[PDB]
Structures are given as C-alpha cells and as structure tokens.
Image (cartoon, rainbow, N blue to C red):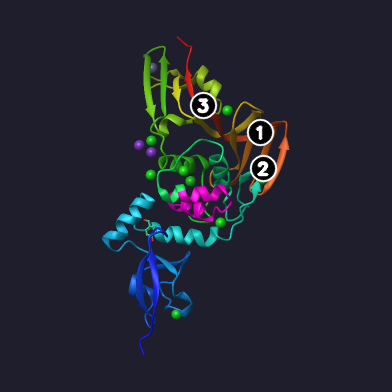
Amino acid sequence: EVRTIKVFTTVDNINLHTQVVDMSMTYGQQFGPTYLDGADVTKIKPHNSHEGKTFYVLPNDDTLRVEAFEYYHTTDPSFLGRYMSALNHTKKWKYPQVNGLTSIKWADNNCYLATALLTLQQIELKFNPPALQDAYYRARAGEAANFCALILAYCNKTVGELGDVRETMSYLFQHANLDSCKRVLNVVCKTCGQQQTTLKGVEAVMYMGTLSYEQFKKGVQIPCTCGKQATKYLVQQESPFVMMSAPPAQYELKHGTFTCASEYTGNYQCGHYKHITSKETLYCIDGALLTKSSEYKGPITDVFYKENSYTTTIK
Ligand SMILES: O=Cc1ccc(O)cc1
Ligand SMILES: [Cl-]
Ligand SMILES: [Cl-]
Ligand SMILES: [Cl-]
Ligand SMILES: [Cl-]
Ligand SMILES: [Cl-]
Ligand SMILES: [Cl-]
Ligand SMILES: [Cl-]
Ligand SMILES: [Cl-]
Ligand SMILES: [K+]
Ligand SMILES: [K+]
Ligand SMILES: [Zn+2]
C-alpha cells in the first residue's frame, strides 16, 4: 500500500509550497536536506503527525531561490543548515526582560550575543533583510530565539563559540541601512602635513583605538608612514550613534556621558562580556543578572554614544 501525506515546504516560513510525500521514503530522498522547526528530518520518513506542517528545505528551484534571497539577502549554500543548527539551541535559551530590554540567560558562551542584542535595543538601526526585520521585531517583544539563530548564521558562528561584540556589531551593521552615515577625519603630521578622509556607512560609525568620543573630537595619536606620531581628529559626523572600540582596558564610565558599553574580562580566546547601560543610574546587565551603581570602572572594550550632527571647531 502506498501512503502519502500533504506537507508544505518553505525557505522563508511565509510562502508555502504544497508537497505530497510518500511515507515509505525519507524526506532527504524527496526534498534533500529537510528541517522541522530546527530539527534535521532528512533521514526520517514522514509521520502521520507531520500532515499539514511546514518544513524548511534548500532553494532547489528558481521560485525558492528568489524567495530565499529576497528574505535573507544571502546565497551561501550552507546558510540553512547553520541557521537550523543554531535554532535548535536558541529555542532552548531563555530571554528575560532586564530593565525593560530583552536579554539572554547565559548559555553556550552567548554573552557576546546578549550584549549585542541589548545594545541594538538602545541605538537607531533598521535592518535590510526581511528575515532580520521580522525576527528583530519579535526579539524586542521577548521571543528572540529566531533572531539569535539568524545572528549566529549571518556571523558564521556556531553555538558554543565565543564571539566578539565589535565583530558581531560589524556584521549587523553590514545588514542595516547606514547609507546616510558620514564621517570626516583629519590627520595632521608635523612632517607630512594634513590629510582629510571621508568615511561612509559602517565605516562612519565604527572606530578602533579609543573609547572616548570626546578624545576622538580632541585628537588621537597614531603612527604615520614616515615614522613619526600623527594626530587624527573628528571633523564632521552625521549618524544617529557612534561606536568607539578599543582593546580591553580599565576605563571609567560616567553616568549620562554615554548610552551603553561592553565590558570584557579575560583573554583573546576565552572570556566573558558584560553590558553597561546609562539610564537613571548605571545598570550592569550580565545575561539574566542585573546590578546597579553610581560609578563604573572596568575593562571596557566598546562604548556607544548618541549623535545626530557634529561639526568641529578646530580650525
Ligand atoms: O539562504 C538562506 C536559506 C534559509 C532557509 C532555507 O530553507 C533555505 C535557504
Ligand atoms: Cl523514520
Ligand atoms: Cl522589564
Ligand atoms: Cl528592523
Ligand atoms: Cl523565542
Ligand atoms: Cl566574532
Ligand atoms: Cl542586507
Ligand atoms: Cl555601509
Ligand atoms: Cl550618549
Ligand atoms: K548597508
Ligand atoms: K549600501
Ligand atoms: Zn608623517
């Protein structure tokens, strides 16, 4: 007897594709790699309980290729497997509301993700892939498992791998509309003179070398190709926020002078991130953990600042 059930395949979990599957063959024999809300059913034969459910598959016809690219903005053939493999884990994570923000209870070295997710909720940023727009909306309401799985997939990180917040923010910014952001810098060398540079997009909102936005406006010392020390300072800035990053160092965070910041304790390959947010006082969010203080000092590695338009007075 040949038995069949009706199921739906998908790449974006919105547009469904009707399939009648033979229950005597695995999903893999019929669709290739097949996933049920994260679980790999490629080697499973259809159950009766599967009738009417949706399965993710690879984009193995033109319709699915277009649906997949329009939704995810990637054509990495390995994305689906990485996304599903992460989602199996992030579905089991907990997403507490901490001081009104969606956080992540610690698991699987996910501190860098919690700090990034907390940061996102405090800066103005619109994602370009509908997949991130949709999942981020749900993350803000507290159901962040799909968003975290997507971030892991876009960043090419596996669950358990310790990521870097700055790197993660860079990936997130690459998938956001920052076309309006503009930065103008001046570099002054006593030997070589002045050199002005204009940066746009992601490069206009990220800096590596100093944590202080004020010091960046005043001027920072950097090597010149002639061997001497040159001074670089901020000429103009058009963006809704800036990110200042630096190798972890003892740094003093003052209430009201910044938006939020990343603290990193440990060494290059192994450590722990914490998040500091400046509200009515200074709150330190460490996954599900929350403490408060009037002053904060610790190994800070990223600081976020609000911005709209800045123009130097340095002549
Ligand atoms: O390219 C991303 C992608 C995501 C889910 C799929 O089912 C297939 C492709
Ligand atoms: Cl089976
Ligand atoms: Cl709350
Ligand atoms: Cl968005
Ligand atoms: Cl969730
Ligand atoms: Cl990383
Ligand atoms: Cl994008
Ligand atoms: Cl950009
Ligand atoms: Cl600020
Ligand atoms: K962009
Ligand atoms: K662009
Ligand atoms: Zn020089």
**Residue at 61% of width from left, 48% of height from top?**
103
Amino acid type of the residue tagged 3 in the rendering: Glu
Could you give the CA–CA distance between mark 1 and mark 3, rounded to whole angstroms? 17 Å
Circle nearer the N terminus (3, 2): 2
Amino acid type of the residue tagged 1 in the rendering: Lys
What residue is shown with label 3?
A: 307
Disc 2 secondary structure class:
loop
Asked whether, in this view, residue 5 is left or right of residue 275, the answer is left
Asked whether, in this view, residue 47 is left or right of residue 60, the answer is right
Disc 3 secondary structure class:
loop
Q: Is mark 3 within 8 Å of ligand 9?
A: yes
Q: Is mark 2 within 8 Å of ligand 3?
A: yes
Looking at the rendering, the stretch of residues picked out in magenta corresponds to 134-157
Image disc number at residue 37: none
Image disc number at residue 99: 2
| Residue 4 drawn at (x, y percent) | 38, 81
Disc 1 crowd, CA 10 A, few/some/many (<14, 14-19, 20+): few
Disc 1 secondary structure class:
loop
| Residue 218 drawn at (x, y percent) | 52, 17
| Residue 304 drawn at (x, y percent) | 55, 32
Q: Are marks 1 and 3 in contact (CB under 8 Å)?
A: no
| Residue 87 drawn at (x, y percent) | 50, 59
In-front residue for pair 135/187: 135
**Residue at 64% of width from left, 29% of height from top?**
253
Instruction: Establish if 232 lies above or below 263.
Output: above
Circle nearer the N terminus (2, 1): 2
Could you give the CA–CA distance between mark 2 and mark 1, rounded to whole angstroms? 10 Å
Circle nearer the N terminus (1, 3): 1
Image disc number at residue 279: 1
**Residue at 35% of width from left, 87% of height from top?**
2
